[PDB]
Image (cartoon, rainbow, N blue to C red; front, side):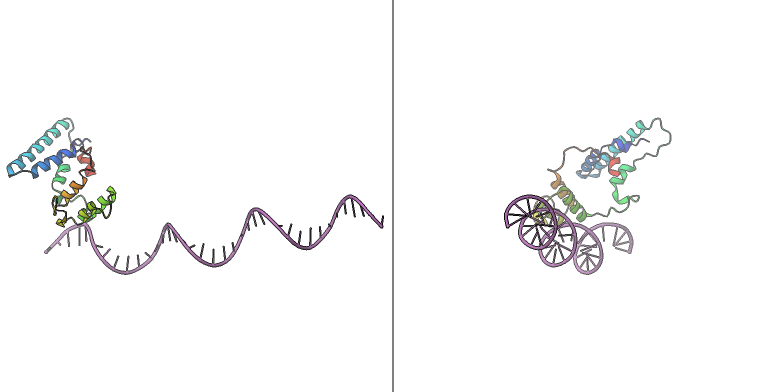
Length: 144
DNA sequence: AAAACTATGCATGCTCTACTGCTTCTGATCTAGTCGACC
């Protein structure tokens, strides 16, 4: 029961999403998405040459590209505030430190750096010096 | 009549077992806030 999702690094999907976001018009975004889809379909055809009945599809990447349409998964129960709290606890950052305060009151523009309304940007800035440069996770592992 | 052996009461030290006070862990309650989904 081989699945293409187990052979696709998550970094590739992240890079594709970043390229789509950092695009001017619809044409470039559609081109990038179509290139990714064609690569996935070619890999699917190559992998499943012999097997007859296959349940493998593009769902593993689709459920991440469009999280709002996910129905199989239940509510995560965590939003910006809970995620910031968990990041503070796990990273062992000081409670009263600058990073923790920035993460908690992310809407306050007191920082004057990055973005004062996008929590993901601040999380990325905080984690830049505390995280490696290359990942080792696949789409299937992230879904699990 | 004098000397040697033995008995018993009290002093001394040590060790072991209740009782009171201080410190720390656990449980129960309340109050404040967060997340889900809809309209």
